[PDB]
Amino acid sequence: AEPLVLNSVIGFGGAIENGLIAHPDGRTIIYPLGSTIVLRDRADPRSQEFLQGHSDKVSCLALSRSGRYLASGQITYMGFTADIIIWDLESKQLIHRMALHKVKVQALDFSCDERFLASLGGQDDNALVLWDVASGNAICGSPCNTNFTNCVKFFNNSPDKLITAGNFNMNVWTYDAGNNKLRPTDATLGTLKRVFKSVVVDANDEYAYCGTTTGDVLQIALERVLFKNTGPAKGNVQMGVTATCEVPTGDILVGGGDGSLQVLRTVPEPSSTNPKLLRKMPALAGTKVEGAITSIALADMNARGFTFFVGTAMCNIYKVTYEPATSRLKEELVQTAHNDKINGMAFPNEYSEVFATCGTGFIRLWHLTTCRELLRIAVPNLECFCIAFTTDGSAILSGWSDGKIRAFGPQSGKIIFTINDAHQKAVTAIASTADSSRILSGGEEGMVRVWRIGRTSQTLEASMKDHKGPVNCIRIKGSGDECVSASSDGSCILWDLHTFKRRTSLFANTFFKSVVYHPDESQLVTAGTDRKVTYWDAYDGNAIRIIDGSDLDEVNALAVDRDGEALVSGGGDKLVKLWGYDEGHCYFVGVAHSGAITAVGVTPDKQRIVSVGTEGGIFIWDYQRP
Amino acid sequence: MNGDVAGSLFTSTYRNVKLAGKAPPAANLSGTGSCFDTTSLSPARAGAHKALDVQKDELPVW
Amino acid sequence: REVISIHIGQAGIQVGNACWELYCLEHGIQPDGQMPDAFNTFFSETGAGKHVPRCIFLDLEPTVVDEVRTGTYRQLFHPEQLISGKEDAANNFARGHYTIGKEIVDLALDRIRKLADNCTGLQGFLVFNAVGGGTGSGLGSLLLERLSVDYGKKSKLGFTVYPSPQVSTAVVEPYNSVLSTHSLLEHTDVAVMLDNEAIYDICRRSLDIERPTYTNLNRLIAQVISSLTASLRFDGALNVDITEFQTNLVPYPRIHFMLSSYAPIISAEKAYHEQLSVAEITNAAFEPASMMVKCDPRHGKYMACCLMYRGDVVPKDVNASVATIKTKRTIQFVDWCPTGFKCGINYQPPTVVPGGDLAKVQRAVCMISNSTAIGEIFSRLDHKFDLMYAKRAFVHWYVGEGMEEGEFSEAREDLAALEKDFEEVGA
Amino acid sequence: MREIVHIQGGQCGNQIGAKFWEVVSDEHGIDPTGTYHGDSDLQLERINVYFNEATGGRYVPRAILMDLEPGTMDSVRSGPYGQIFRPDNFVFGQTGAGNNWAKGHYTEGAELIDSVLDVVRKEAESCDCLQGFQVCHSLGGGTGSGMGTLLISKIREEYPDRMMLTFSVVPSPKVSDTVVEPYNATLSVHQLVENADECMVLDNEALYDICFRTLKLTTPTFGDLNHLISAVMSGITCCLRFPGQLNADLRKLAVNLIPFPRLHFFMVGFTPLTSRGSQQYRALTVPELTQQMWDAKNMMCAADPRHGRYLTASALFRGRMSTKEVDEQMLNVQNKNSSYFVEWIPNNVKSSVCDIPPKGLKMSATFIGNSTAIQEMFKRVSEQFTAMFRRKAFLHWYTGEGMDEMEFTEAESNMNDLVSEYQQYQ
Amino acid sequence: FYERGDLPIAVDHRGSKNMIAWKVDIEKLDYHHYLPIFFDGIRETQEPYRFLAVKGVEDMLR
Amino acid sequence: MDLKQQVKNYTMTIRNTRPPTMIKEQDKSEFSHFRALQVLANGDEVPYEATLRNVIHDGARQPKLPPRQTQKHPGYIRNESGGFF
Amino acid sequence: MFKNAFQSGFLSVLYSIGSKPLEIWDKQVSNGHIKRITDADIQSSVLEIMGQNVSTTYITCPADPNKTLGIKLPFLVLIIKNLNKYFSFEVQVLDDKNVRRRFRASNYQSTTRVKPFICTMPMRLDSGWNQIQFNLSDFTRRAYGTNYIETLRVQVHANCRIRRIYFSDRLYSEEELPAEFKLF
Ligand SMILES: Nc1nc2c(ncn2[C@@H]2O[C@H](COP(=O)(O)OP(=O)(O)OP(=O)(O)O)[C@@H](O)[C@H]2O)c(=O)[nH]1
Ligand SMILES: Nc1nc2c(ncn2[C@@H]2O[C@H](COP(=O)(O)OP(=O)(O)O)[C@@H](O)[C@H]2O)c(=O)[nH]1
Ligand SMILES: [Mg+2]
């Protein structure tokens, strides 16, 4: 019951528009993880307390100008109103929860005097609702447009606001406390039919800048809402303009949809001796970024340069310094993580500071001690499943969704061999035997295959098809004879190397997910969606004892210590259980992985526990006695 | 070799100003005044190349 | 002993895409083209540490061809084997036989020329084409004509895909099938029918896949071809060659249309289920629920039959099995042939393809027979052919290409004459 | 290798084409500036069909824009995916025809078509092996129908051996915008039956009906109607641009669907079409696609197919599918509704499978039916034409420009014998 | 020259020792241009080539 | 057949003779990246840029689909006699 | 290259109607220009090479200078337009003695020289379009006792409008020539 101390945390969401946001004062960065926002000390990488409270993924963020109040919204199941939560950054408490938007809250924004909030929500809802922050009340609401709208922003005097469509319109909404209504005036685009993504208001509200999807910045003069010269004269940007921030000077830093940064001069100028203004000439074409830019935030105020924190859809936080004296951008990425959900992780035998975490299209070799990612190899568009080292450090085996098993080298990531058909579909479990000559594979078909890897060829030996469900896990014994396969049938099979046969089959009402040998092959520990951990006698097969731990949702991760005194358990919920082996007892930790945890392990030297959830996060814990 | 030369005047000018989007050179409109009334004829000569470079002090010295 | 195999059309190249996968799997050839004497009938070893197949894939669209060029077997085929035109025949026999054929066929046969020249003990040709399509029928018939005027004497095993009665993916395939058969008659020596309804039922019934793609069809067709060519590839207790089908199965110079079958088509669980012996698989190879052409041979009488065996098979039980069958009366032979069977045994069992659904069986049978059920099939196609020609439908596409109605009428009366010959021989 | 040249005429053609090139560029993964930014390599191999490669790794569309007023050209360059067109492709008049078929075929054609022919001919020789021409236009407008029709006649006079598609909307009395709709449609139909290879007739009443019932949208703006027609046109050429298990060329579709050189007027459909509110309660299976496909309320014409017979039909599927399911489903729909097909043509359903679905979905299809219920539409127009031409109403703006009365009488004759021969085959 | 393919030669592949199908007739052939070629090909030991060379020489001389 | 395909074939014959290449594209180099690991293990002051090295392989040509469902719930459909395929 | 091709009666190396006509040719333009325009007398797109100095601007047939195309066809046929300017074209050929001769046909010389590596020939043209046929084998047999084996490269110089340059095996006449190789 006692909470487990949480060491380092690696992972953040970049897919969210304008998600990465900085604190107005001092050292604090904050980004949304799966369904909980995470504070971090800007100075040193020491994780800060998380803010729980969301039922599902957070999909927007907003911070007051003073930095006292913070607002966030979530995306929910279709048909259930999503709620905005307002936190206090002095006392980290859920202060107000308000649910009006049907499906998802598209974006939020604070007033300059922090008196009001604005929430626009729903790819289908399309309703703008103004809230007051003093109490969880909503002032007035209005259906915005026919086509959907993306982002809103308040002015810097804050009677008014401006909103833009996804598709084809843009309005400025003024608020008067006489009717308690919102009066819109739509912009006068001469003939342009652009698709807007992001908008930012100036430091003095004279213009606004909206990034179209066509790839150009559009400057809109305010008050008459009349459009003004367009963005980069030297062609557009390679994708839709997706990120925009305003330099404290008369400049705007725009991040295109394909990892491109540009500083744009905003002061107008007539050229060719004409009444016509020329296009905004870019004062500096910043260096490129690998990921699609989604979030830009101005971090620091320094007279010799300005630093910005830039998030990417590839989930790579960059710091960029802009020196206005000599026009150049220097970029250093400080953190990276997974973009999509991850599944499966691996440990090298009797080695500590290496991780093999593989999500969609990527294998990643992490260094545990510092969390600095070392090596990432990508197959373009494919889904990775069960990853596993070989007992000898050479091969890193990885299954894939197309049904091919591929083995890579840990250094240089050079693929050594591939099986152009391991299964008819995705393979879900792969295991290396101690002598590294045999390899066990299991796909969704439910067939367990064994492959003998020859020094230049790889051949298939007998393949058994006991299961009718997708094989969920495969575990081999110290000697090469024994391997157990856990599938969604509700059965676990024990096999025999010397004769490709089965001895017995463990049976449960619910599908078996994870299965682990006890050290020294005395017993088996199985966990499934029956919410019930089960001990089994390794030799003849029998239900020793059924523990009802974590009855509320399914349990899919079992890890066991090297001696076998403790047993780490993942769950369908967000908490990590730490049981003693001989007795059903708890030492668990609750607050982590806003999304369900999918795999967990303990380092061979018994110092740390490592967990990976259905959101792109890896949580290094501190191991202790049970 | 065009059968009718003026057949392109409208479309070609409209294309450069709008289709291609290139900046249209819009000069030599000084003194034209309004329509309905005579443009004051300037004494300038169109053909003459009155560059007459003056690098008074920008000339380097031998 | 070497045989070369050409593939013509969209179907032919995909069947070959499965055949050559199975071949390199049997002789242990990695897809890059090297091993880590039995192969010599298919793969010539040129230079050093390299095996190239004896085949040409040809088609007029580049789509499926450069799919092979960029698929798994890039390094395997020599890039000049894969002929590709510019535009389809598009279900038009005359377009495939006169317009584009005249430019592509010379390149094709002057490529197979140096194929046969590199060969030394050429056994024969075997072609793969679907007559429902445009190229596989049109320029397939053009190529067969020019191959017969070149060699003539040699056996040409044709594994052709016919349209099924009710399951169909084209509309003019009656026209294409009849015009192809008008040349399939007097050019090929041995022509094996392979329909699609029958194979769908097989993979639904025995292999119990409910959603089968063309991949599964092509896989077990590759099994049939390998099962009837393993006699040349490996040494058996009783091996029979490709020139034997020419002799033992074709009693008359025009009656060469063979119903094929294969057993045991068994899933992975039914392998542990059933006790695999020789008597029952020789029985299973005779029921219409295991044949590759959708027809009922009970209505017909057999003319000749050939049984290839693979695996651990002694000749005693096959003697007993065919004894019981010849004593059975559920199937009847013709009076013109008392000895209607031809056995053949090979030692090696059939292999499994990782990614297939067939389990490792110790023994297998491949039956290639002759009957008058085919005489029923040709009447079924001819009936629906005259239905369309009664209204002169679709004729303008052919005439617009340059052909006329003369070859329509003469192909029609040709199938009529063939029908008369089938009903005359069956008596 | 096989090349499609796209021609857009009139305001409707230009706005449809704007959405069509939008969807195509989205499928092949090129940005609205003209650079490839996809990830898979299936999209590189088959952009030569639609985009002449240009310096800078820019793929510009192979389309010829054709109209008479600068208003539509501004609306073309305005919207997104507007900066990708080559500016010299904008073949272009100055005044506008405005619902006058004579002004689209005798007055302005004689001085605009030399120019548009030179760009089309020059664009044809820009690619190696032509597959066919593909025009999108209307039959009611003036600058679209008249100008496009004389273009069709000149092209078929030049390149008689290449296929020809015409995506043509037709007037309906319920959605009747202009007034001389029969005067423009009849003369265009009389010319399309003698020059076009096959015609994919569209109509706005059926599209609005579809958006009311199946989509359940509140306000169907023109952006949505053109989006559906855009999905149909992308469905008809998915096979040339993507490998599949049964590839169907355009000429392969023509020979399977045209039994007689004049019986080439199709009706088109598209699936899956469901609201957001029902996107979650539905599955993605071939029967679900097929039940929606053969539904009479999913045709994009104002012609009930149950009021006539199907001569031939074709279906183009996209997505990882099982061909056995495809064939047996077409087998079931052919055996259950046996009375609605014609008898003297066996196997009236040609089908095809492609291995790439359109973006945003898991699986899709496209129905193209050469039925004989389309003669209802042509009767519905010809009866209006006769109503006016007994009076000679509106006739003088036509006969005063060079056209004679014999054109109208012959057009009536050709429309009448055409619907008579559809009725004969019914 | 055989690689280039200008030789009117093919193999019959008969049951006996295969013979040479001569595309053109042998009598009207130019011997000044071909005899040296075939006689130079006798040095070959590769299976597809030496057979053709020797049989062509034999047939021409006969 | 045509000039286009002929030059394609020439290029591909050359490309097939060459031994297969393990990497489609290589970022940085193994040696440069290896040194960064050495200075990291030796001490501090190593930018994240140097340690993180990425490699890209061929992978599948296809775009990405959600996995196809071959079989539905066994209660809905059975073969002729019965059973769950 | 071109050594594993078929090399039938006709072989086209450059044709002015295609997605990339100069796909194998390596252009060398200096004080000149290259275009694909439409000629007003045949209503077709021709490739135009025009430069001040004839010796500077040209287009060689195989792009990589070390790589050499090998073609065994006797006759070389060019379809060009005479612009009353200076124009030349050159071909390398291989003899039976494994030596490389060059044949340069030029518009602006009168003499006919025979040199160990180069045979320079005069060439006169008509006014409009014209197809020229070269007969490589006979020119080799005349300028040297040797005979023809292979053509290694071909290169055309400035001031000409070219389209469909191609090899052949016979002196084809018009009626027996196919359509796409004919003039009109
Ligand atoms: N057995 C089998 N038959 C196929 C396969 N693919 C296509 N077919 C058959 O081929 C017939 C039509 O001809 P296709 O092969 O598709 O095309 P084609 O023969 O090249 O003729 P064109 O399309 O005009 O070029 C159809 O009846 C299909 O049944 C396949 O993968 N396996
Ligand atoms: N679907 C669709 N139909 C249109 C559009 N614009 C016009 N139309 C239809 O086109 C018909 C008349 O065409 P018209 O505008 O006169 O063509 P044009 O004047 O020759 O360019 C009317 O019935 C309109 O309903 C459009 O953007 N989408
Ligand atoms: Mg085909």
Image (tube, coloured by chain):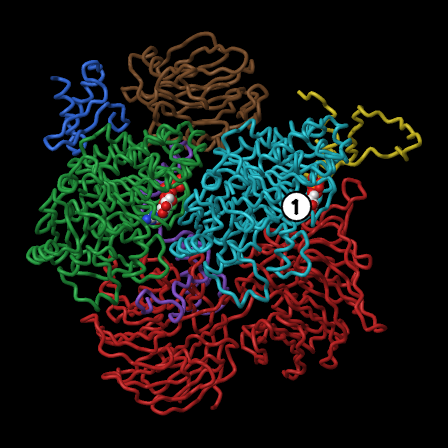
* Residue C105: % across, % down: 33, 31
* Residue A217: % across, % down: 68, 54
Residue that sits furthest to the right in the current view = B37
In the drawing, does residue A28 fall left or right of residue C415?
right
Q: Which chain carries label 1?
A: D
* Residue with the mark numbered 1: D15
Colour of chain D, in one word, is cyan
Q: Which structural element holds mark 1?
A: helix
Colour of chain G, in one word, is brown
Colour of chain B, in one word, is yellow
* Residue A140: % across, % down: 76, 73
Query: In the rendered image of this protein, does residue E2 appear above or below residue A354?
Result: above
Shown in blue, the chain is: E
Query: In the rendered image of this protein, does residue D341 appear above or below residue G133?
Result: below
Identify residue type, mark 1. Gln
Shown in green, the chain is: C
Shown in purple, the chain is: F
In the drawing, does residue D372 fall left or right of residue A266?
left
